[PDB]
């Protein structure tokens, strides 16, 4: 169907960042232990909390 | 491969080349085809050769 | 779109917008710890190591490296180490045989998966066996990218 | 007149190597005349950056 | 308070030790047990005490 | 967190195409536009805890 | 402060949100990889027996 | 780099007229606007593609590896 | 192999479309934006002549 | 006490059990039965991600100095108090020897492996009645060459006595007694690239020199007694077989070597120029 | 065929210490063995 309003619409320059989703998705349950404190360890690299 | 391009790049480049499409009803979908791995009834085969001459 | 979100055309993504390479590197090298004999880049057998991973070590070759161009999953192994001590009752003391590994083989980061490419090896500053690899991985843009 | 001068060569080369590796700006004296951000890792993302 | 606080206890004569979990050996991943700060300093304390007792 | 808000409970409808999803209503007490901020989630283990989260 | 009145936890999730106009307030959208990763204990009753057996 | 295939905006086959679009500059001394006219893409949606593509594959390939 | 256009644009034959009805606003399903005049601030359709003013 | 934990599944008992480790959850499971044995594993990589004891010994070294939130009036007292316990240990002399072999090896630009192997060679004996002093530098001159050679690196005597004048024979007897010490506690081909390094030549003369040295080692004509010199004249006969002016006086002054021995080797390979060239 | 090392399109077939610095070339970097083994790809 016809649209009521009208739209400013056209070519434009964009660009891409670095913080992609796969480095930020992170979840954990009952994993590695730090020997000093008996708590879950840090770091997305070694599967932290 | 030997070029200064990579291989799946060449693949996605290949993927958009259209082909002749008259008798496309005659062949069958691979999902419905009883066979496995591209019988002559369900697919066609392509060979490309280039050289650095 | 609300509060600066974005609607996109997945058909344009299929046509080939915003596709991207991703190179990652690795630093690895050997040491002298004796009684001067250094480590080795061996291909592990079943009876080779100490405390072996579940790396499914078939992707390596006789030089202890991976041939380029094959695909790797996240947990897969690429390098192989072995402890050269000499003297610590080398392969008959406090362990089975499984000779002298204490194996510190580097797996890939367990999420990303792709194609290894163009593995180079060259001696370091003092002269050792020093190894760098590079893995290539396509990342198609997805729902959660910062634009 | 030879034995000392080549370890002197090690001291000068090792000192400059340590300085431009770390960014601690001084000799081996645990951050004296100390200011840190002098030896940043070069930004290598985009030609413009 | 007499039962818990009397100033001769406030002066140190006999020193307890901390257990191995508080000062754990990190097992530094090629050959070391990786001894840490607290055990290091306690070893310094014992060395200085045995030096003083032999001297006197 | 600043005040009594930012601590909501929720039910769940499980969604594919991996990311979170929430209602446009609650956005301003959450005090977060979609500029890439990240969330934190927790799951109770026993029924007393699950009930008191549900009721409060 | 970093160990007693706050610390690390378990059963945790951390992603980035998008809006939606079709989910009401008490729901939340949760991605299925995270739903595979997480867990929740239950109990075995005469009531839940068949659904739990099927899910096992 | 390589002039791409199948325009994001329209989608017709693009790059047939590419080295054509090249050789209508040098041996013809021809202005680009009438040159795109005679080239014959009456939309603009594909006209922009060749307008803002920048070659990189020449600077790529004038290495000598292997 | 076979493939269809709906799951991927590789098998799309169309790659263009044009669509017009009521070039002269007689059905009046929408107005036009204007700042001083509806007529002069817009161009005529190419399909103008086949229906009367 | 026997100091021993053995892990065994209490329901399979087929062997010392075929078990695996799930490091991603830090647990261990008997792979046959599928039951856990123990939980909460301790990491074996994060400590190396977190941060020479064998040569410094069981006693541990400590250098002390100044900081920011301290006073100069007592850090100078600390600087004069840092030597109040160096006489309690022989490790002050061990680290003085370590510092001096560091002086020597980095003076001869030797790498970290050569430095640590010389440290090992001193730490090996460090005290015998066979050692008995002997100027204290003869033992280090021996130890640096021992660690160099066991690093598969060859260095000349003439380099060693250019570093320290050890009168060449206290050095020799120290080398003999150290050779007996190491054998109780238990190669000249690489000289050639350093010679052509000092002479500045491409590869094919060096490969030809290695091939001719191998062939002359195989056949006959020791003829020079220390065949270092007949190696050197194999380079001489190779460079005279080519057409680069590396004349005999220049070679003799460059290598600090006898030109009459060069002419003797030139005559004995002038006889034997036949079977020594591959292409 | 095990090593390339250089601009040569030569199958140098080096295995162990046969003048690693390449003979008909001038290189000391030892390029390694583009793989004969068949690969799999996935172009979806
Ligand atoms: Zn078929
Ligand atoms: Zn177009
Ligand atoms: Zn079992
Ligand atoms: Zn070469």
Image (cartoon, helix red, strand yellow):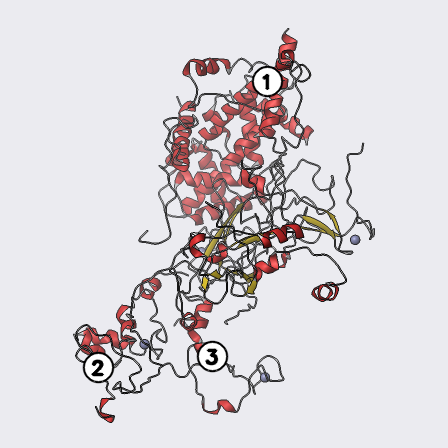
Ligand 2, what quadrant?
bottom left
For marks 1 and 2, give the one nearer the viewer. 2
Task: Check disc 1 and report its element: helix, strand or loop.
Answer: loop
* Quadrant in which residue C38 is drawn: top right
Question: C4 or A16: nearer the eye?
Answer: C4
Circle 3/circle 2 CB separation < 8 Å: no
Provide residue C132's location: percent of width, then percent of height.
50, 51
Provide residue H43's location: percent of width, then percent of height.
27, 79
J30, above or below C124, in the image: below
Around disc 3, counting alpha carbons within 10 Å, would you say few (fewer than 14), some (14 to 19), or many (20 or more)? few
Image quarter hosting the C terminus of chain C: bottom left
Residue bearing mark 3: I6
Circle 1/circle 2 CB separation < 8 Å: no
Give the chain of mark 2: H
Tag shown at residue H38: 2
Question: J169 or J181: nearer the eye?
Answer: J181
Furthest-front residue in view? Answer: F55
Answer left or right for C57 relative to J2: left
For marks 3 and 1, give the one nearer the viewer. 3
Answer left or right for I28 relative to E25: left
């Amino acid at each position: 169907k016809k649209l009521m309003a009208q739209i400013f619409f056209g070519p434009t320059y964009y660009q891409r960042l670095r913080h992609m989703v796969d480095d930020k998705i992170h979840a954990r349950a009952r994993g590695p232990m730090q020997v000093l404190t008996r708590q879950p360890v840090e770091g997305r690299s070694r599967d932290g909390g | 491969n030997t070029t200064v391009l990579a291989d799946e790049f060449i693949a996605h480049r290949l993927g958009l080349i259209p082909l002749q499409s008259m008798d496309i009803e005659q062949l069958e979908y691979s999902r419905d085809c009883f066979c496995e791995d591209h019988c002559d009834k369900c697919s066609v085969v392509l060979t490309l050769q280039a050289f650095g001459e | 779109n609300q509060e600066d979100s974005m609607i996109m055309n997945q058909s344009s993504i299929d046509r080939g917008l915003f596709r991207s390479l991703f190179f990652r590197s690795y630093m690895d090298q050997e040491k002298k710890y004796g009684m001067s004999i250094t480590e080795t880049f061996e291909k592990p057998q079943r009876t080779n190591t100490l405390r072996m991973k579940h790396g499914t070590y078939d992707k390596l070759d006789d030089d202890g490296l991976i041939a380029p161009g094959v695909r790797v999953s996240g947990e897969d192994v690429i390098i192989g180490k072995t402890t050269p001590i000499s003297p610590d009752e080398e392969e008959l003391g406090q362990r089975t045989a499984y000779h002298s590994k204490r194996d510190a083989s580097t797996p890939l980061r367990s999420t990303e998966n792709g194609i290894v490419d163009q593995v180079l090896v060259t001696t370091n500053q003092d002269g050792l066996k020093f190894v760098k690899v590079r893995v290539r991985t396509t990342k198609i843009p997805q729902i959660g990218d910062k634009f | 007149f030879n034995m000392k001068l080549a370890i002197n060569a090690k001291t000068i080369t090792s000192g400059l190597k340590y300085a431009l590796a770390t960014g601690n700006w001084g000799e081996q004296k645990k951050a004296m005349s100390s200011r840190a951000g002098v030896s940043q890792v070069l930004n290598r993302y985009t030609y413009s950056s | 308070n007499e039962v818990f606080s009397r100033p001769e206890w406030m002066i140190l004569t006999c020193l307890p030790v901390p257990p191995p979990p508080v000062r754990p050996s990190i097992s530094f991943n090629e050959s070391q047990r990786g001894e840490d700060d607290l055990t290091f300093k306690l070893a310094d304390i014992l060395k200085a005490n045995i030096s003083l007792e032999t001297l006197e | 967190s600043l005040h009594k808000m930012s601590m909501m409970a929720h039910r769940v409808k499980v969604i594919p195409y991996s990311t979170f999803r929430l209602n446009l209503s609650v956005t301003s007490p959450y005090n977060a536009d979609f500029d890439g901020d990240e969330m934190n989630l927790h799951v109770p283990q026993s029924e007393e805890t699950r009930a008191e989260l549900s009721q409060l | 402060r970093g160990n007693l009145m706050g610390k690390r936890v378990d059963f945790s999730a951390r992603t980035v949100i998008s809006g939606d106009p079709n989910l009401e307030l008490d729901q939340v959208g949760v991605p299925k990889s995270i739903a595979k990763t997480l867990t929740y204990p239950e109990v075995v009753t005469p009531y839940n027996i068949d659904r739990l057996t099927q899910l096992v | 780099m390589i002039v791409p295939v199948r325009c994001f905006s329209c989608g017709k086959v693009v790059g047939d007229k590419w080295e054509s679009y090249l050789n209508l500059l040098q041996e013809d001394e021809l202005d680009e606007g009438t040159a795109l006219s005679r080239l014959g893409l009456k939309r603009y949606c594909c006209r922009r593609m060749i307008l803002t593509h920048v070659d990189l594959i020449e600077k790529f390939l004038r290495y000598n590896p292997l | 192999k076979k493939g269809i256009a709906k799951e991927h644009a590789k098998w799309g034959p169309a790659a263009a479309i044009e669509f017009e009805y009521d070039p002269w606003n007689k059905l009046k399903h929408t107005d036009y934006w204007y700042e001083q005049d509806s007529a002069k601030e817009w161009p005529q359709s190419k399909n103008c002549e086949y229906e009367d003013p | 006490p026997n100091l021993n934990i053995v892990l065994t599944c209490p329901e399979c008992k087929v062997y010392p059990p075929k078990i695996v480790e799930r490091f991603s959850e830090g647990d261990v499971v008997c792979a046959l039965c599928g039951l856990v044995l123990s939980d909460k594993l301790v990491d074996t990589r994060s400590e190396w991600r977190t941060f020479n004891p064998l040569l410094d010994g069981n006693n541990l070294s400590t250098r002390i100095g100044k900081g920011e939130t301290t006073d100069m009036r007592f850090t100078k007292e600390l600087n004069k108090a840092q030597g109040k316990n160096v006489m309690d240990k022989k490790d002050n002399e061990v680290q003085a020897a370590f510092a001096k072999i560091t002086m020597l090896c980095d003076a001869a630009e030797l790498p970290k492996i050569v430095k640590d192997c010389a440290k090992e060679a001193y730490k090996l004996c460090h005290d015998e009645k066979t050692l008995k002093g002997k100027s204290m530098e003869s033992i280090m001159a021996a130890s640096i060459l021992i660690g160099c050679r066991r690093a598969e690196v060859a260095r000349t005597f003439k380099e060693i006595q250019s570093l320290i004048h050890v009168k060449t024979k206290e050095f020799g007897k120290t080398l003999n007694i150290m050779k007996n010490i190491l054998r109780g506690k238990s190669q000249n081909l690489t000289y050639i690239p350093r010679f052509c390094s000092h002479l500045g030549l491409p590869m094919q003369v060096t490969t030809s020199a290695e091939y001719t040295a191998k062939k002359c080692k195989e056949i006959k004509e020791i003829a020079g007694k220390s065949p270092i010199t007949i190696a050197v004249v194999s380079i001489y006969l190779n460079i005279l077989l080519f057409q680069i002016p590396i004349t005999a006086a220049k070679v003799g002054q460059t290598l600090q070597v006898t030109e009459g021995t060069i002419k003797s080797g030139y005559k004995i390979l002038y006889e034997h120029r036949d079977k020594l060239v591959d292409p | 065929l095990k090593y390339i090392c250089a601009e040569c399109s030569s199958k140098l077939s080096l295995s162990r210490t046969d003048a690693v610095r390449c003979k008909d070339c001038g290189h000391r970097i030892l390029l390694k063995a583009r793989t004969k083994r068949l690969v799999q790809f996935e172009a979806r």
